Image 1 (cartoon, rainbow over the protein chains, first blue to last red):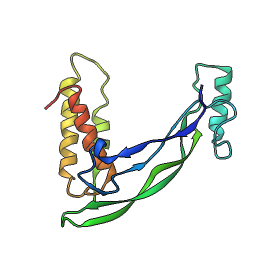
Image 2: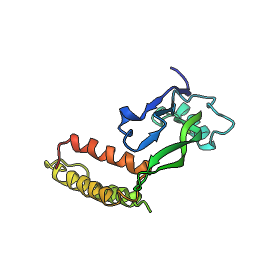
Image 3: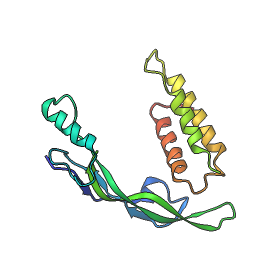
Image 4: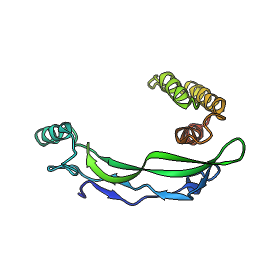
Length: 104
Length: 70
């Protein structure tokens, strides 16, 4: 089936129940990773030797599962929140958005 | 300073009981859930803009629904 790819995902903070503390943005394009990790591995330039060993082990013994499609390149986003003084505060939140997917 | 990791680690420690159910883990897990909920509510003022905290509150009340506790 479909190999390891990045897929769209818009996180609306109001649907998730975070509109009460996040002033801005109303949501964000987080994305998600999903898909089969057969030989050769997706993001093979950065993929771990262990994933290479495990997908080889899987090819000999199906009881051992293949490597898994997860975010391998992430990016941060700036958000606004209110503090005790009811004042808006900017903070950068690390590894919020997926830039690339790979097998791990 | 936000002390949310302290609450989670304590909860992960207390929730090391499988499974049974007698039944069971309902009176055990909901005690662990309330302890966690209480700990997060105590560090509430310090975690004003902490993502891991705001995820813990929605995570706790989600477990409180299934199975029913409090």
